[PDB]
Image (cartoon, rainbow, N blue to C red; front, top):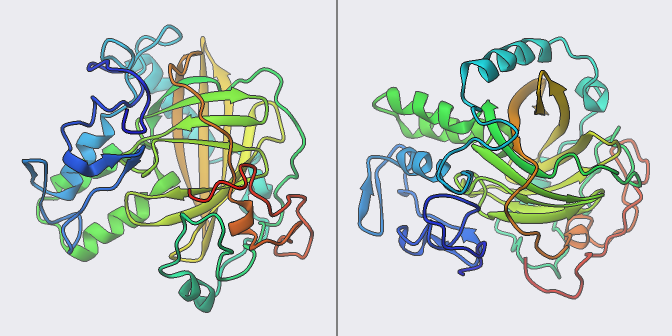
Length: 351
């Protein structure tokens, strides 16, 4: 109910209405829309009776929503102890190996990255991102040079399952900020912006994958929408709990790696990103690497189950809005990217 996953398990499982009944009206129609003190997350707030020392404290509690197995734990049949010392050591080694890895997407992010102008960002301020019938005010978003074209269809659905974050989780960064006692507005604002969206991870991911189409359950502590479905090469909209708005795309050009990008509309920045799955010892890990302005942020997850224990939702896209109705819009080097500016779920009107 409430647009969330069907189920009443109070101990765990995919996010459902019973899990968030306690947060007054913050959760509705599958969306998480909380109200943080006008000033910033450093200032306190109150949700359905419970007062929170700060907005960060609310986010910390929201991080615990939706990623647990049926009995309230985080482990699964493929890895019963994701937070154990064994997994930690493998993760530390992968982290160190990540700095020397020269196989990253976009030619290790050296490909020329597009950026929206000051005017373009200004035009979009206040735009109704939920209206599928509107063209983005700044015209077609630039596709990032070096993005592979779509067409490949994964054969083994390797992303399908439940993944638990073992490095780069946002809660760890929030706990650091909280320990910093007295935070100022500027300070809180920077923490939110620096760890926003894919710069850090939620505590889990549940993925339903069928070839080049996936449904992904992500942390509502970070993303306003609990569940999203997208298709390789097609746009989708990510409203953020921070108030930010992203229009991005995932391409699945290979069997074990996704390559994509997300336009953060309020800053005009194009974050480029990849997710790859690979084995280490008896486990399967996923490394997420997000880059902007020369800075690469890594998130690591360990696969705890082949079952996401969450259902897919209908397919959609936001190619019309994002490309402002322009078929085969270009990359920033003037090369046409083969995606038509029509939403896969047309004529649905709202997103």
